[PDB]
Each structure stands twice: as structure tokens, then as C-alpha cells.
Amino acid sequence: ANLLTSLVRAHLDSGPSTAKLDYSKFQELVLPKEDAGDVQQFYDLLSGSLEVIRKWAEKIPGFAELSPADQDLLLESAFLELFILRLAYRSKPGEGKLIFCSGLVLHRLQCARGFGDWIDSILAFSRSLHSLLVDVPAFACLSALVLITDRHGLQEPRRVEELQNRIASCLKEHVAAVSCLSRLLGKLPELRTLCTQGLQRIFYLKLEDLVPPPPIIDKIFMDTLPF
Image (cartoon, rainbow, N blue to C red; front, side, top):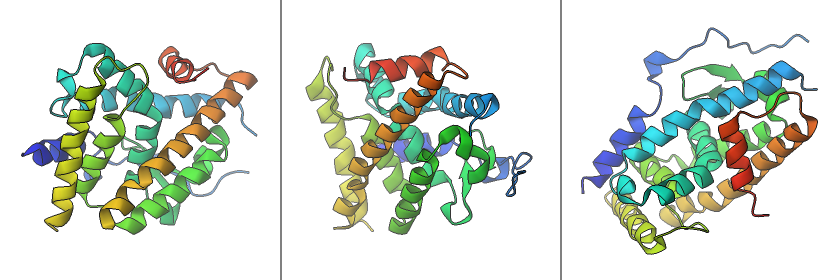
């Protein structure tokens, strides 16, 4: 298919229109470590992608045909990595500009306190991703592949594999219709590492306990700790 087309439409609909960007809070300069407002903003930014990613996923053909327990596991396990990857692709690392799925635009310095060093690691991944010049159809497949992947505790792991195989096929085909490929999906391993830095940041913040995580983020955190 045609799957490609559904994948592209799912992606485009899950993000702001360039016309939809909000720069009312954007400030490149900052007068002059984290306080409770930085922490609450960190949780709010994360939180805003929760509903968005879920709706995006439901539009990936075959995802809603996975068991509902496998759907939830897949979503929870991939959430950070998806948040990071969609953010890296959407943002403008050359200007330190972060663009969130709501359309809100923030400078790196405005998020640094809440995010810690992770934001710099994310911006480094974003420059690298931008160097590959991943076109929208390739990215629509790649982001899907982050979600539809093997995980521990899947009820029907072969079906997840089948759907993954379908999306990988579609991607590889689109790449021909235009080495590059292996380069492209070598990004997925780096993405997992960045997910780890995110879990590390949430741990520190829970440790610190200025503002507690909201229940859904907290659950993602606890569920994804292999111990």
C-alpha cells in the first residue's frame, strides 16, 4: 500500500501547522538550578504529547488490530523515544529552537533548567537527524517503527513483528523509489540511548521532588524500569 500514504497522513495530522506556530512565549535571552516552575513546565511539555501520540498510533494501519494490552505496552514503552524523535525532527537545532507538538515554540535556554543536560543531547540528535535530510515519508515510517517494535511482555510478538516487517518494507521501497537506509535506521539505537537519559532525568526530579510527576508519566516511568 498506500500504507505509505496512511502513514504520511497520520504523521502530518499529528503536529502543528507551520501557520499554527505559537511564538508568544519565545524569548532568546534569559534574565538572568531548577525551581518548581521549570519542573512543572517539563512535565507539561511531556504531557502534551501523550494524547497526540496515542491518536497518531491509532491511525497506523494494523496498530488498532493488535491486542489492546499490546497496544498499551507498545505506546508506553515507546513514548519517550517518540517524544524525542518527533521533537528532534520538528525543531530547528541551528537556532536552538524547540518546537513542541502544540505549536508552542521555546528557546533551548527556556527549557534547560527543567530538562537538564538532556536537552543538549536532544539538540545534538536533532542536528544529526537534520543532516540525513529524512523526507516526510521516510520519517512517517521511521517513527512508526520506533512504536511497532519488539518489547518484553507482548502477548502476540509475531503479529507485532509482521506489522513491523510491513512498515520496514514500505520504507525500504520508498527509499529506492527515490546505505542510506541502514544509515537511517541506525538512528533508532541512538534514540534508545537518549530515552535512557530521559528516564535518568525523571529519576532525579522524583528524587528531588519539587513537583511530582503526573500519574500517567509516573506510570510510564515505573513500568519501563526493568527492575
